[PDB]
Image 1: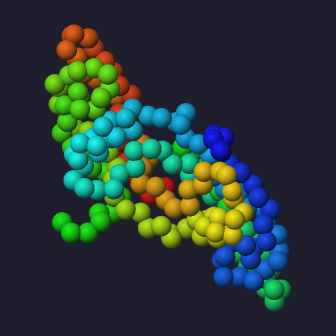
Image 2: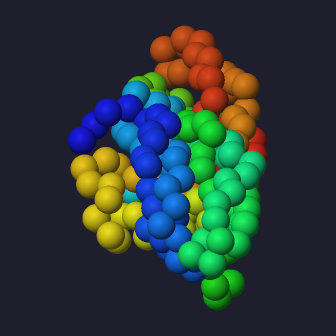
Image 3: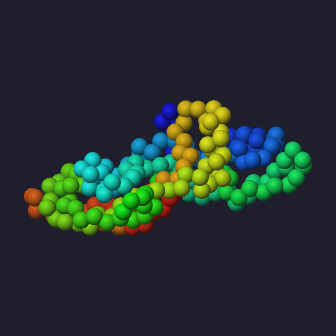
Length: 99
Length: 101
């Protein structure tokens, strides 16, 4: 799809996140997804024109914006299968942008 | 040198015509851009996104589950004179700072 880059939310079992934890506890996971065509820049035009002509000393360059978090949630706490209290830092996104 | 350079600011002298902005100009600018490698597994958020995707929970949306080497700031303006002696000011043409986002 091509909905614009933004914050999305999904209710997930923490065992689905693959953190190494067995947990059937549900957490609200927030993430960044979507299209960045409206976010086109003159920088990206020039960079694409230079990569094509082999002017960038064979380095990997990103000439298109990426939809990514600009900020993260500080803490997500949950209990595991042994009822042990756990905290995870910067699990969910708090804000998104086409970078 | 042999090996992938880490994400950072790079500079290159270019004629404005080379940038393909729509105007021919032989004026040389120092173009600055972001290039290089980012460690793909530096984030618990990216690990979560990766596992959700492999288990087919995020279908149909464009999702970036690794950091991108991109500008975090741009140089304000770049001005130049074209072949018709017409003045142009281009905003945010060159990067000022880079990061793995």
